[PDB]
Length: 282
Ligand SMILES: O=C(O)CSc1ccc(Cl)cc1
Image: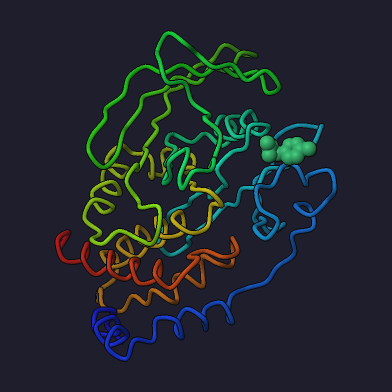
């Protein structure tokens, strides 16, 4: 079916639950043996969220190559994304080591450092120009250059220095700051606007490494981000835009990382955003 009237009519019969469950029932299952080694326990935020062996990002080091991060590779759409958990205090250095090695241009953050009174991820970037951060274990330096604070998101300009070779690179930090503590946004407007600002920077482009995206666990809000972009990019690519099947796209993406889209509310928002962005950017 066209994705607009599946929506009008899921709300109507209201089977959002039902639909979301079939997706869970049909999603891929692949091994995660590396994530589950004892030696990595402390490297995972959540015990039920792990990267598949086949698609995990490997750090370049003899030590331990492990990070909770997955490469999502969309073939027809010609877009790749790295989805990862928000970093822990002990893993911050691994995170930036990963950004350096994969040659990413942008980092996209869909959550606040603190939500609902608990820590959602480490404060992993510097907040004042004159106070730079240094990751000792991976031998990197990170400096804040500038920042643009707008009402629904912020953009930061950062400098990452490989202290071993003295090479420097410019990283963009795209920080969506207003997703609610509970539930999903009510309108997708601002989310839509954020998404187009990321495209505009060149961060999602092939002339760079994959974009790094994350929230808490790296599956819920992060999955909405990548599903939406890919669905909107496919729409413009096909002779008939209406042929795009979002459930099909989501199940493809779940071949590369478990659990993408965590609630039916999030599934709904995804359709809603795609339906709306279709008719605008068109
Ligand atoms: O949770 C943190 O603070 C970082 S993860 C971690 C968990 C357990 C141990 Cl023993 C060390 C780090």
